Image (tube, coloured by chain):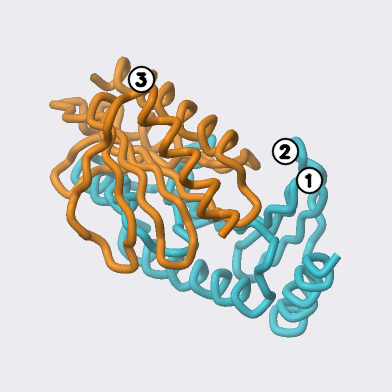
Chain colours: A orange, B cyan
């Protein structure tokens, strides 16, 4: 309800600064909404239990496997930071970085930060492991 | 408030089934509570902004390569599952698996499941990568 309006402002806002989003098909279960902002390779999903998700695609990375795999999977070290960005590998060895956050009592302004934060992180990660 | 009583029941309950917890020192910033259940190698932290955390230590990485490391960092694939368990590497190449969840409107019963779920996962991950 208040969460709906909040989630809307988020979207509305990203549309104005990244243009119209794309609307992929219901892939995952419990999924109810999915907006794809292709310019920045980020997808926003909304759980059926009111959780918003941010998925970013870093892209492909060749070689380096044993090389830096660790330093990569080392980015998942524990810490008490809000919106933690998990770094993982796609179903085809492709860079992927996401987060999830309940919508209850979370305004669009923070969701934007989370989003932006996610962008920047994808940047930094992209320009290191290629 | 209601979150306090909730978090308490969680703890109280784990105490009864895993005995007295340990109380490490304020390591991370924003940290306010930390309970260590050494029997199961899991630590529970509580953010200053009302987020509960579950940290599990898989232990020593004796052998690591790139068909293993990947398969590991492959456990972080995206999906719309509640309480997502991030698998990462300690500050000394040591197995580590954690999650975080806001306390607002979350009962101790679900928190337990999350906990238990985390245990089992640490199990499965432990008996495969060591």
Tell me which residue sits at (81%, 43%) in the image: B26
Marks 3 and 2: CB-CB under 8 Å? no
The image quadrant where one finds the N terminus of chain A is bottom right
Return the residue nearer the eye: A104 or A120: A104
Q: Chain of mark 1?
A: B
- Mark 3 — on which chain does it sit? A
Q: CA distance from mark 2 to mark 1?
A: 11 Å
The residue sitting at 77% across, 72% down in the picture is B6
Asked if labels 3 and 2 share a chain, the reply is: no
Residue B48 numbered mark, or none: 1
Left/right of residue B44 with respect to residue A57 in the rendered view: right
Which residue is drawn at the image coordinates 19% and 37% (left, top)? A94
Residue B100 shows up from this direction: no
Q: Which residue occupies the foreground of this view, B98 or B108?
A: B108
Label 2 Cα neighbours within 10 Å, binned few <14 / some 14-19 / many ≥20? few
Q: Choose mark 2 or mark 1, whichever is in front.
A: 1
Using the numbered discs, state the Cα–Cα distance from disc 3 to disc 2 in whole angstroms: 26 Å
Q: Return the residue at label 3.
A: A123
Res A108 → quadrant:
top right
Return the mark for residue B28.
2
Does the rendering let one see residue A66?
Answer: yes
Q: Secondary structure at mark 3?
A: helix
User: On the picture, is A60 further left or further right than B90?
Assistant: left
Q: Are marks 2 and 1 on the same chain?
A: yes
Relative vertical location of residue A115 with respect to residue A130 in this rendering, above or below: below
Q: Determine the residue positioned at 64% across, 56% down.
A: B102
Crowding near the residue tagged with mark 1, few <14, some 14–19, many ≥20 C-alpha atoms within 10 Å: few
């Amino acid at each position: 309800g208040a969460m709906k309006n909040s989630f809307d402002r988020l979207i509305d806002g990203l549309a104005k600064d990244y243009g119209m989003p794309g609307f992929p098909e219901k892939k995952h279960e419990h999924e109810v909404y999915c907006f794809e902002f292709k310019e920045v390779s980020i997808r926003i999903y909304q759980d059926k239990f009111k959780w918003v998700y941010f998925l970013s695609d870093i892209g492909v990375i060749d070689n380096l496997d044993s090389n830096a795999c660790q330093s990569l999977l080392r980015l998942n070290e524990f810490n008490l930071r809000t919106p933690f960005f998990t770094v993982g590998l796609n179903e085809k060895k492709d860079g992927v970085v996401h987060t999830r956050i309940p919508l209850l009592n979370l305004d669009n302004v923070e969701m934007r930060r989370v989003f932006e934060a996610l962008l920047n992180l994808s940047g930094e990660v992209k320009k290191t492991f290629g």
